[PDB]
Length: 382
Image (cartoon, rainbow, N blue to C red; front, side, top):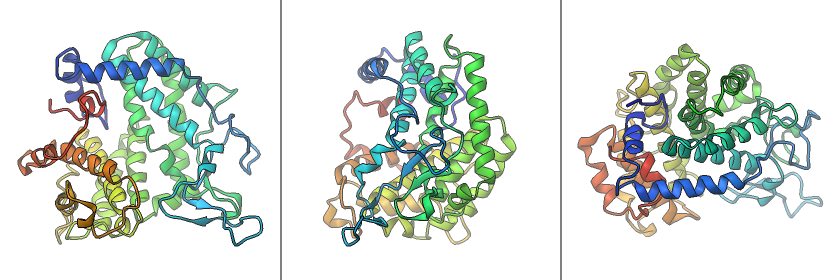
């Protein structure tokens, strides 16, 4: 009858889905989750040691990634400096740490959820192997900083930039997966202490680094995402005062700054994937609403004097959901169907906070997500 202390996942909902794992509603998704976890068992845990290049610190244990939208310039003899092509991801980024970090993060989340749903230690043990290799083992560990996040060839004098902070956004969810495994045997006090210390050092770095300062001051989805991460990592590390403060400042610093009275997010709508970025930012807003609700803080209903809110932002998007791209007057260069589907899940999540608005009935009209998809477990109607 225990509810886990999750901050992004809706905890009471998730406890009820677990209790009803074998019911007809959830059994197909649980089956698929355990198949995914079984594939993860076969994976070899990667590390920041796997990249062929080294950051300009000379320390291979420093995380290094490349700005995904930055490409060689064909008008220059050696392609340098790189130039930006918004929305087009340069596959060279695969040489560096970003995708390995993603595989790890996704594997631990999969494994923690599989453990929660099954109680099978093999899932928790493999998760702990991933975490040891990535975070804790002297041989392979990532240092708790992103000084060299999103380097760009030929630019920024070999240094990272604040934008690289977005690379670890999935840690917000990974922390909830680790909480779900806390009572496993593999997830020991030593491992829990190790992880809390790594996140403690990361937060100290976020609070003092000039590189992290760049992300904190970002005006768009990067800034909003920074606060969500700072909050989640502060809570994980026991720093409730920093969490409370970041939450309390979030409507003025982020929501009211980035959302217009008519719901437009102009900095996202200017992008080549304007629908995708509008949804990216909304999903992170809803992540903050969820964290905040655990501390009794009502971010979802925070409303400016001139009418700016998450409700306004949703109201702007809704008329485009389920409609052809001909009806959308901004760019969306790719992933049209994928982002329409994600919009239906934004509606599911918003319905948790404003049931009366009828968001779920709007999304149910168009949503085609197969019954065995994990998302049904995580944003259920419990």
